[PDB]
Amino acid sequence: KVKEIRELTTAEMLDKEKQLKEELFNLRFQLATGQLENTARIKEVRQSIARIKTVLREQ
Amino acid sequence: MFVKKGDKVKVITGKDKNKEGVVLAAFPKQDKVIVEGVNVVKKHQKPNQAAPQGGILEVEAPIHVSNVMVIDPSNGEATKVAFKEVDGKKVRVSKKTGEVL
Amino acid sequence: MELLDVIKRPVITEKSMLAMDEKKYTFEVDTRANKTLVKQAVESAFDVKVANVNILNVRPKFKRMGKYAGYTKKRRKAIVTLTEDSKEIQL
Amino acid sequence: AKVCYFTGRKTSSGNNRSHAMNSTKRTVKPNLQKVRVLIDGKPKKVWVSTRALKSGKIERV
RNA sequence: GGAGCUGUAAGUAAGCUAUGAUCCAGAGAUUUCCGAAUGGGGGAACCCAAUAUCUUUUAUAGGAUAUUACUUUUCAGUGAAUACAUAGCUGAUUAGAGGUAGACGCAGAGAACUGAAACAUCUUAGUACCUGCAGGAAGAGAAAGAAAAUUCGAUUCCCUGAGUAGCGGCGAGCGAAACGGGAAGAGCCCAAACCAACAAGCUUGUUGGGGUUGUAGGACUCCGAUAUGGUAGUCUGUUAGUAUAGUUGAAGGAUUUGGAAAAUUCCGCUAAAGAGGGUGAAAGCCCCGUAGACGAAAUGCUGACAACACCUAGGAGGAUCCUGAGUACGGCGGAACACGAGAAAUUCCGUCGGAAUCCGCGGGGACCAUCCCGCAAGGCUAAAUACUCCCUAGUGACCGAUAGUGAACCAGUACCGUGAGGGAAAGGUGAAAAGCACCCCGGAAGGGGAGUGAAAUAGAUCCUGAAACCGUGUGCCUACAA
RNA sequence: GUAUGAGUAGCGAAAGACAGGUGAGAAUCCUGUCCACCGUAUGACUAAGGUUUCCUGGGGAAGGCUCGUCCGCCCAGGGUUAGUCGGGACCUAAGCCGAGGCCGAUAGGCGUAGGCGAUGGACAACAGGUUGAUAUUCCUGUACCAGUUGUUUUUGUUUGA
RNA sequence: CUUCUAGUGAGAAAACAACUGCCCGUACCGUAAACCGACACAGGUAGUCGAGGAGAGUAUCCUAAGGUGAGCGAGCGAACU
Ligand SMILES: [K+]
Ligand SMILES: [K+]
Ligand SMILES: [K+]
Ligand SMILES: [K+]
Ligand SMILES: [K+]
Ligand SMILES: [K+]
Ligand SMILES: [K+]
Ligand SMILES: [K+]
Ligand SMILES: [K+]
Ligand SMILES: [K+]
Ligand SMILES: [K+]
Ligand SMILES: [K+]
Ligand SMILES: [K+]
Ligand SMILES: [K+]
Ligand SMILES: [K+]
Ligand SMILES: [K+]
Ligand SMILES: [K+]
Ligand SMILES: [K+]
Ligand SMILES: [K+]
Ligand SMILES: [K+]
Ligand SMILES: [K+]
Ligand SMILES: [K+]
Ligand SMILES: [K+]
Ligand SMILES: [K+]
Ligand SMILES: [K+]
Ligand SMILES: [Mg+2]
Ligand SMILES: [Mg+2]
Ligand SMILES: [Mg+2]
Ligand SMILES: [Mg+2]
Ligand SMILES: [Mg+2]
Ligand SMILES: [Mg+2]
Ligand SMILES: [Mg+2]
Ligand SMILES: [Mg+2]
Ligand SMILES: [Mg+2]
Ligand SMILES: [Mg+2]
Ligand SMILES: [Mg+2]
Ligand SMILES: [Mg+2]
Ligand SMILES: [Mg+2]
Ligand SMILES: [Mg+2]
Ligand SMILES: [Mg+2]
Ligand SMILES: [Mg+2]
Ligand SMILES: [Mg+2]
Ligand SMILES: [Mg+2]
Ligand SMILES: [Mg+2]
Ligand SMILES: [Mg+2]
Ligand SMILES: [Mg+2]
Ligand SMILES: [Mg+2]
Ligand SMILES: [Mg+2]
Ligand SMILES: [Mg+2]
Ligand SMILES: [Mg+2]
Ligand SMILES: [Mg+2]
Ligand SMILES: [Mg+2]
């Protein structure tokens, strides 16, 4: 969440962004197949990346 | 709306006048509310709804919020609602008795 | 753009499944991605080695629901052929 | 534009009046001349009206 | 703000939410590509680059980031014919391009149909259109004025003068202004003379001081004052208010009809609230509101306060000096003044000629004299005035679906045209989908039952359901009639 | 909006026949057989143009001048694979744009350098196979063009390849 | 594109091995029912290939490859056109 993002460091935030991007890629593949159940997780991950990028820019 | 989910309300207009029940669902945008056992409708349902008969189901339909009044939990009677801040928290108050909620 | 954003999703159809038997996989890719970028993205994402990459532009398809008619989004389709001695992509 | 570099004179529209007072639009032009003059210390050919030159204060390099 | 929420838009599916979501307001971040589009190109939303850094690969290929249009200002460097230089070229710097609101303003250019019962002067009309420039307003504005009551004292706009004075193939028509009454009100800066500084080439350019006028002013020379007042200045602060969300906000139960009460009847109650809207029919007391009270973290806007900033002198003498030149004015040709060359002032443009300067100059409708009024050829200036694409809150003896915007509805859409362009039709089930389970005929469509509903001849071509038109049934008549 | 004409004109150049099948339903859809038509075309390729009309599976509301079980229609999925083919990262014609510039009430007109612009010039791969739908594009086989890294063998290092 | 020097130059060339090579189009109709003619319209639509007998021939008749039976029919066999 936003509080945790602010706690993290610059390098930590960048690594978290990469991890979330990979997870979003995996979710896209699972949704393309029938292997995804929690569809809302995609929007959650996208908004999480948005929060991380917003914090990065406001630093 | 002045009435809220889970409230005990009295119907003051309609075929179900003077009945009392708990609020099951609230729709502020429509200014409507559903009270258990109030305004029940027979609905001709095809069996496509996981019920392998379809049948004639019975369900409560919403009624306009203005047609109900919150039941005083302390007195058990319907009353109008004022708003008083109690101990720094805004709450509903019965105009007939002054009890909260 | 980011490599992880280059590839959007796989394509599962009869033609794509036959491609897989020949060890080639069909992906929908960003419409601005060229086959060289697609090759780089596939290698990074899947650890495989890419032998070749073919790419097509799928035109928007006209559709209509009731009284409203429009076009499906244009797409870019890439068939990626992996070399021998390469891990298969798992879906 | 074909405008006096100093006095700002420029082409304008007038009337042709016959003895019957019939009116038709005409163009009335100033008497401009291409003259080599010093602007900010450098020579240049610019349009200048004979009226502007009349005083003699405009250098004639 | 306090309980639901993931739009229209149901449905499934998956989720969020008192750890305060959705939602509302202020601020901020991201904001692909085209488009003035501006690295170059281009058939807009596409293509291809150079330079520098970074990234993928063993490496080429590949990717990301930043800069790179043209012109204007300024500076600097380089630098031709040519010696000096300039011009060019390079870099940096500076501010412009484009769109609007089909409105309002100023200016350039500028019709015809039409009227004259024809038509050319004239009128339509300096209108329509095109173009440039703008500002929130613009334009005008501080007398070379209006007058001749003796006076007034910048401009603008309104009423009036007045359809008058006048203009006009003296036709058709066009048509003032001053006085008077009002809205609003505000006055100020330079050029010049003179002094000082600076540089060059005693004057001759820059800077500063000085001066801004007609009951003539200023310089200059004497004196005396170094005040008194003001501002049309500032992202200067403080303060108050206000705009952009909101909070609170009185008082009704029964009775009869009805599917349903607000309607009827009976008794009540509130009102700083009996505006309005919704609710199963018509509600002061059911809901949203209204009167009233209250409220702003954040950003705007306004007014005040202070701060800073900037303007602000009195009296006396003229010997001399200054007071806007190719200007005023005149000829010629046009144009604007209500005024069409007319006796023609006044003002403007083009061309040519061309003054005086305080014993001076301009105007007072040709012109001269006297008298009176004013002081051009430099600039700025708020308010009263004009308009509304927009946003907010309202109003209507304004329209109510062939009306009202073309468009109440996915309308400048469908459709038409190569293109500019032209341009529609189309609102209403029910209180509530309770949108007809199930059965029967049928392949379906569509019906008949059975149900929902107060009502289904309210069944989605759905409120009402007219006429034309079509059809069924029949009380009377009709196959010797024009 | 609905009549009248009126159940009238018309149903747009030509050969179909029968058997079987499907289907609620068949002159009209499918299969078969014979017959007939075009064959410098009514065949096979392609440019432009159209823009999914292509393939598969469903459907018979509307459209098809009849019918329709069918379709270039409707519904749902799917389909276009390039270093070598055409175009761009190559060149230019006509024409067009046009830095400065010339000209001009405004707007703008013209035009140099420089560019754009093919219908032309230059340019490396062909045969076969494969799918329901793509193929000098995928696959098989065998090539060619441009270039990078490496190994080796050669040869030049400033009278310098 | 091939040469010439000017310039530039410490690395070039050959063989071999391995490897790299971007963007747009690619469906389908295309002397037509899919384009231009409002139509599934007797019209128009550039270029290529376009066979055999007789034949000068791409004429003409009948055929090959290949394509097609034309999106209303069944009767009757009057006038009239
Ligand atoms: K452009
Ligand atoms: K407007
Ligand atoms: K006329
Ligand atoms: K007339
Ligand atoms: K002004
Ligand atoms: K009048
Ligand atoms: K007359
Ligand atoms: K002064
Ligand atoms: K109610
Ligand atoms: K009411
Ligand atoms: K404030
Ligand atoms: K005159
Ligand atoms: K005067
Ligand atoms: K009804
Ligand atoms: K009858
Ligand atoms: K008719
Ligand atoms: K008829
Ligand atoms: K079918
Ligand atoms: K060509
Ligand atoms: K193809
Ligand atoms: K022969
Ligand atoms: K022949
Ligand atoms: K047929
Ligand atoms: K007959
Ligand atoms: K006949
Ligand atoms: Mg391709
Ligand atoms: Mg560009
Ligand atoms: Mg006339
Ligand atoms: Mg402005
Ligand atoms: Mg209240
Ligand atoms: Mg009452
Ligand atoms: Mg006049
Ligand atoms: Mg003159
Ligand atoms: Mg005069
Ligand atoms: Mg007089
Ligand atoms: Mg006087
Ligand atoms: Mg003003
Ligand atoms: Mg009506
Ligand atoms: Mg209308
Ligand atoms: Mg009825
Ligand atoms: Mg009706
Ligand atoms: Mg008889
Ligand atoms: Mg009889
Ligand atoms: Mg007849
Ligand atoms: Mg036919
Ligand atoms: Mg022939
Ligand atoms: Mg087909
Ligand atoms: Mg089919
Ligand atoms: Mg039919
Ligand atoms: Mg040109
Ligand atoms: Mg094919
Ligand atoms: Mg093809």
Image (cartoon, coloured by chain):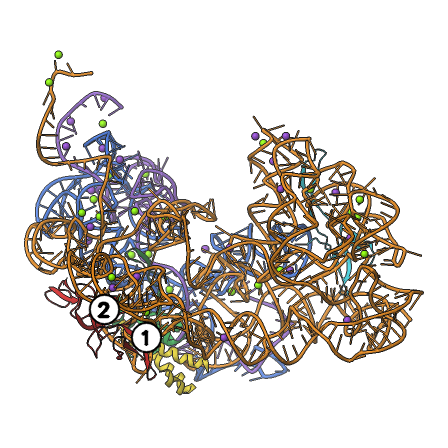
Chain colours: A yellow, B red, C green, D cyan, E orange, F blue, G purple
Q: Residues within 10 Å of mark 2 (few under 14, many from 20)?
A: many
Do the dots labelled 2 and 1 sit on one chain? no
Q: Is C50 on the left or on the right of F18, as rendered?
A: right
- What is the x, y in percent for residue E206? 78, 71
**Residue at the (25%, 77%) spot, across then down:** B97
Residue located beneath label 1 in the image: A43
Using the rendered image of the protein, determine whether residue B62 is visible from the camera's viewpoint. Answer: yes
Q: Amino acid at mark 1?
A: Lys
- What is the x, y in percent for residue E92? 62, 74
Q: Vertical placement of E72 versus E359: above or below?
A: below
- What is the x, y in percent for residue D16? 70, 39
* Chain ID, mark 1: A
Q: Is C10 on the left or on the right of E237, as rendered?
A: left
Q: Vertical placement of B21 versus B14: above or below?
A: below
Work out whether residue E105 or residue F87 is closer to the camera in this orientation and state it. Answer: E105
* Chain ID, mark 2: B
Q: Residues within 10 Å of mark 1 (few under 14, many from 20)?
A: few
Work out whether residue E175 or residue E354 is closer to the camera in this orientation and state it. Answer: E175
Q: Is F94 on the left or on the right of E81, as rendered?
A: left
Residue located beneath label 2 in the image: B68
Q: Vertical placement of E344 versus E444: above or below?
A: above
Q: Secondary structure at mark 1?
A: helix
Q: Vertical placement of E437 versus E195: above or below?
A: above
**Residue at the (21%, 78%) spot, across then down:** B73
Picture quadrant of residue E72:
bottom right
Quarter of the picture holding the N terminus of chain C: bottom left
Q: Is E175 on the left or on the right of B81, as rendered?
A: right
Picture quadrant of residue F81:
bottom left
Whole-number angstrom distance, CA of label 2 to CA of label 1: 40 Å
